[PDB]
């Protein structure tokens, strides 16, 4: 089967119990709820239909909450009509949010435009459609020299490549969505426009302040500032989502492929889950089959090493959402089956988990059984891309859902684990029940014995 | 200095002496001539303008001719207006070329349409826009049931995924173009829609018959039949072109990307050139910048190991030919400078060449100087992706040109090389003259000594 | 500090409790009893004196019983006088044991002398002093032509190089000596003159019938036939003793060094103990310091990989018993400490035991703690020449004694181990009690969990 | 055939042309001349019969001269009677060369005895037979306390363990022996009792000052002072001789075995010849067959990596010199056929010669042919212990002789070599004539091209 996990953004056409039941059947693993739109009654009902489907069907899934996040936007123009800009003209941005725009001026929502920017910096409007150079800055106006032609519309996003922007890490609306996340008991939170480590902690504080300590934080990297602080941002998050489309607006186009690859590699080396997202199968919002391009992009993303691939509009609003998940599952299976283990890499956990993967492959073990509380143990084996499927045994309900996103992982919640010998017994029974192994197969069993929950130190080889 | 080579299809906007020179300044190495269109006055002019540009400046490049080839196409419709075909409807193809089409029946260009097809096959019209199922075949009619809605127009290509097609290897015009190739001294010949080894052999007989025995044939793989027989085609060809676009229609969408990787890998091991083509940076036909998607696709083909990447419309019929090349060349460098040698893989030529690269690397040699007659020696080294640049000294002007298409090779024509010790003298001098090495650097020099051409047997180390 | 173990033949000057105590202080590990000489009261007394010192001191050791074995010997001469034989003369051996010899004929003790030999064989008398070539065989006589001059004495041993001899596998006296071995509870039994597997099985039967199922058989390979069947013999024994001296008499002198090197390496591979003996430090029978050569021979034995090195007369019938053992311990200490682990060379037991040693080195673990019943698991670790010391915890007292002979092993007997977590608890306490580890050191612990005795499947890393 | 080379000390029973002829047929390669005894006419004549034998048959050998060297010896006793020394007694050595000795005091030949020695140092007389500890030093006498009983005889050697001895670097007679060496054109010189680099330099000055500039210095390591300065001594010398007998008396006995191995390895890494000498097959001075210990001591010296093994009294003054060499050859061979290459270890000669050997083995070439004038080229290849035999082609007659001592090297004198391509021509022809390779076999050819002598930079692979 496939090992790479599929995040599906759920929307009006896919929030029914009947659809979610088939969305999982087709390969969906994590439900994404995009709070950029929708209201608390909408999502809470979507959450309920899934937990209804899971309870009745017996399948497992995770639920991810994604924040709107901070952003800079233009506003309206006179007559609400587009305006055509010409290169070389002088253009001006104003802080005054009460101004209606025109061909010489438009208003912006963030006052720190003047302080953060400096003469020589570039300003990009509407996903980089129109670019401009800042030539002078005065009070409540920002003077620019237009660099390229384009049609400016109303309420368009603005980007400042290579510039340290001083936005708040979260908007006030974000704070309320996060709190709703804690009340619902969500498993993951993906936070938009994370630029620096301080941003990651502020979310962690807020979740800690409302019972979201056991919630894993997924930081979305979207610009060069985030990329520049990526190492620190990874250290502070529980995982990463690579938002390739947005970064493409911020950095040289040929670096994006090497930005995604590095980040995947660094998440792998760190035993932290990674999602590759945006411009995945966009051509399928309207079409029943994807491009040659889209599938190859996805296939290179799995070969880079990502844990998960994410469907956005394709599944929340698309006209062929079920076909999108299904073909994604076909791409993942086809791509996952020709990848090899990565047995390189002094922690005790690292030495033990890496050796167990080599031993699994040295014995053609179809399954590596892992006892985990917080999930680090299943993620330590995953770093080595084992051919074996990882059945992770836990009593912690959150852990089981969160491992739904880790590559190659099959979570199974169990009542209790009393000792090291019990783990081997219980795991042996369950290895047969899971159907992934059979009598006569070898399994490798990883646990921590007489050590804290944070370390993995034991490896044992059993026959089923 | 990039190692990957760029093929550019030259057209009206890029056929000037002044422009071609600016394409070469920008990194162009090979001129492609797409003989689907244009006439002998047009093509002969491009060849002359290049040789004028080459003659005056001293830069060197290659000339590749790309054939139209055999094909199956629809014909004209009533009133020359589009007709909408509906899923479930019955549609029919006819052999009678004087029949006007309609919503229920159209004429085809291939008379063997009925005999080649069988009950159950899929028929695709206009690059897969509309697909149909064959339901019956009788005489001069082909009966089908339409599977998807779309407008069938005039002059639309026909594709038979998973179906073995029995067309001829050359059209009468193909025969006339190749002879013009022989007459003009083309360096390469690209052969479209290669399905079997016999297709390549037919071309070789043709080319040998007009004094172009030394002209390299690069087989373009364009359907599922070619892919099944790829191994035999490579043996008979001099190289391969991966046509990702055309294969995208003939084979399941999740297989295409691995067909590229597989096909490229075998070209490397065989010491035969491989080009990745079609759907490179198409969007630059209209836009002055590529998408993030394209540049990741292109560069990942370089990481696969491709020798050369090809521009089609971007440089033939496009608005931004210089911008297309430059971003291509910048992608080649950004990608090439992070790729490593591949020093695995009982022959003499290989053992010496693999040893020469490993020695050069262990001694921080910037350069491998190679004495070659037909270039087989330069292409044996290239297999291992050496960090060091290859200075290929030859007395055969065709080889000097043909070796411009291979990755990392800087060819140099010489008056003579009388002996092995003579080669070391001259090769050391020319290494310094090129500016690619400097006094004191280590250079590694590979030649055949006291053996006929085609074998490389000697490897030597000098300080400049 | 040393890892190689020292076997000592104990004799009149070293059988007192006061000596045994100082021999262990000097490095002795195993006592050997040469049943070639002595009677049941002497050997039984040595066993008692050692076990008294063990009881008083708390030190541990093993008891090895070495058999006389079968043999072919000359017999009595006229007047008990030496006779001089001359090269070229005819000499005759007779089966008639009532014939008194002289310079033309002597009797032998083995009735099969006439049948086993053939015309052309070599006959060697008195440790190779005198050689003869068989020229004819008639009735009860073997006729020979003497090849070199020498003095034939009374009761001289005979060697028949390259001849398959039909002697019994055990002497009638041997049968009783082994029964005494069982009665006393010896740990090892070394069996002389093993030629074929059938010999080893007869010994195993004999031990079974008197309660010696737990006694390990150590087969002494002493002739060409022993060597030819070495595998068949090794498969059935629990170990090997290399009889260097006799091998010099049976096989070309250039092969003996390569018989030894093999036997050690194949014993290493089989997880079965190997002892190197004979011609070790003979010169210390009379002198207080060994040869330059002797010390070099002894050290190359340890480097080949032998588990233990053995002293004979040096410690049994000699003037400097403690000085010899002491210098032996100095050679072992000095030699062992520059030897390296061997991390090469399907089964489960092997995969884990090689991984535990590879884990131990990557973590600088000074000790590898093993729970073992029958000693196999502790011996499976040693196969890889671990830098670390092996602390083998067992409840089988015979195993605890027998494991004193395997290189690098420290036995410690315990009451019980009820489970895998219990094993880790106690092992950490007992690791520190031994003084071989300290707070902060890492230990690796090898066990069998939920499998029967004979398989090793679990390895675990703890910090003390 | 064997690769290890044999040095033989030649004497009266082994100086006849007929016997030298039989010594070479049996495997003798280098003649040793021990200037401890004999006079210039005797040594000059042995030199003559060899160069006569070489010329007549065409078989080849080299000539080595061994110095007596400086030394400390006791002198004569009263009535020339042995005196019995007892443990604990006071004994005294005197500088006065006019004193006749007795049981309480004897004279020594070295004036610096009092100044070099110190209270607490050990004094050893007659192969370490009697040892004494200095208790006081006054005027020209050194007082001692004897440690063991023993009989002191006349004219006995003295050894001072761990003491920096300030004798001259050469004895006065040695200077004349070297001058005699320069006259005869000996190829090698063994210089005894080398303690420091300055010692080797005094010899080098002396040899050059009399025209022996191309004579190689083989420094004899015999005491602790040399060992501490070994690195410089090898660096300053042309090769090393391991004199195990002398070391056995000067340093702890368990260190001797590692002193041999270390020096053999370091000479290997330096591309400098190493001879292992003393206590090789001594038992054959009196016996026609060697000991198992001796057969193993030598065979382990070859496995250690020695270029040469040396016979002393065995071949100079013993009863079975011819049998000794033959069995020495049988051991060398039996061992030589089981050794493997050692292909580790960024200099140009190193990179190229190591690459040729792996390629030689990757193609099963039975021969590597090397072009050398100063011999460095063959000794760089030999270092990696190639299976292929090194056919070393040279124009320097001395070089051809000096390479007779180097392991696995077959020297060949040739008229001239006019080019690199000439070497390939001639080398292919001579490879076939030599009988070591045949038509269809691969040969690997190593030469230096367009560089000064001392550098090897070219490797070429040819079919015969």
Image (cartoon, coloured by chain):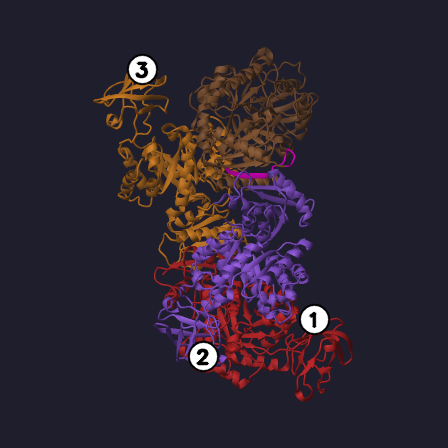
Chain colours: A purple, B red, C brown, D orange
Prevalent SS, magenta region: loop
- Output the chain of dot 3: D
Is B393 situated left or right of B77 in this image? Answer: left
Q: Picture coordinates of residue A318 (x, y %)? A: 62, 69
Numbered badge on residue C57: none
Q: Is residue C340 left or right of residue C184?
A: left
Magenta stretch: give its range: C450-462
Tags 2 and 1 both on a single chain: no
Q: Tell whether position D61 is magenta.
A: no
Task: Please report, as a chain letter, where disc 2 is located.
Answer: A
Rendered image: mark on residue A149:
2
Using the rendered image, report if marks 3 and 2 lie on a common chain.
no
Judging by the rendered image, the residue that carries numbered circle 1 is B164
| Residue closest to the eye, D73 or C314 | C314
In the image, residue D435 above or below residue C265: below
Q: Secondary structure at mark 1?
A: loop
Residue furthest out toward the left: D139
Asked whether the viewer can see residue C17, the reply is yes
Q: Above or below — where is D357 with respect to C81?
A: below
**Left or right position of A200 against B166:** left
């Amino acid at each position: 089967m496939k090992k790479t996990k599929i995040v599906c953004t759920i929307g009006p056409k896919t929030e029914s119990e009947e659809m979610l039941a088939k969305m999982l059947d087709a390969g969906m693993n994590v439900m994404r709820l995009n709070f950029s739109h929708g209201d608390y009654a909408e999502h809470g009902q979507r959450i309920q239909n899934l937990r209804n489907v899971m309870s009745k069907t017996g399948k497992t899934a995770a639920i991810l909450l994604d924040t709107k996040g901070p952003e800079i936007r233009t506003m309206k123009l006179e007559g609400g009509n587009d305006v055509s800009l010409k290169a070389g003209q002088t253009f001006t941005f104003t802080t005054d949010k009460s101004v209606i725009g025109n061909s010489e001026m438009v208003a912006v929502t963030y006052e720190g435009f003047t302080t953060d920017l400096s003469v020589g910096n570039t300003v990009l409007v509407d996903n980089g459609l129109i670019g401009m150079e800042v030539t002078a800055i005065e009070g409540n106006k920002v003077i620019c020299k237009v660099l390229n032609n384009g049609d400016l519309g109303e309420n368009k996003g603005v980007n400042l490549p290579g510039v340290s922007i001083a936005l708040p890490a979260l908007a006030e609306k974000d704070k309320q969505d996060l709190i709703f996340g804690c009340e619902q008991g969500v498993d993951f939170v993906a936070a938009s426009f994370i630029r620096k480590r301080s941003d990651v902690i502020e979310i962690r504080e807020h979740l800690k302040a409302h019972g979201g300590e056991n919630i894993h934080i997924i930081s979305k990297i979207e610009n060069q500032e985030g990329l520049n602080n990526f190492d620190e941002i990874l250290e502070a998050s529980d995982g990463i989502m690579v938002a390739r489309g947005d970064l493409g607006v911020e950095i040289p186009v040929e670096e994006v492929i090497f930005a995604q690859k590095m980040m995947i590699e660094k998440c792998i080396r760190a035993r932290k889950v990674v999602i590759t997202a945006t411009q995945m199968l966009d051509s399928m919002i309207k079409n029943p089959r994807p491009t040659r391009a889209e599938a190859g992009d996805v296939a290179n993303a799995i070969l880079d090493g990502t844990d998960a691939v994410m469907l956005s509009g394709e599944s929340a609003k698309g006209k062929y959402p079920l076909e999108a998940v299904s073909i994604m599952a076909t791409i993942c299976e086809r791509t996952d089956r020709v990848m090899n283990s990565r047995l390189e890499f002094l922690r005790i956990t690292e030495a033990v988990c890496r050796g167990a993967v080599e031993t699994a492959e040295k014995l053609d073990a179809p399954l590596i059984v892992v006892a985990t509380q917080g999930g680090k143990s299943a993620r330590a084996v995953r770093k080595y891309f084992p051919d074996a499927t990882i059945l992770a045994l836990t009593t912690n309900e959150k852990t089981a859902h969160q491992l739904v996103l880790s590559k190659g992982v099959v979570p199974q919640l169990v009542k209790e684990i009393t000792s090291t010998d019990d783990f081997y017994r219980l795991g042996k029974e369950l290895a047969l029940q899971s159907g992934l192994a059979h009598k006569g197969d070898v399994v490798v069993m990883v646990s921590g014995a007489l050590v804290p929950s944070g370390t993995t130190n034991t490896a044992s080889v059993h026959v089923l």
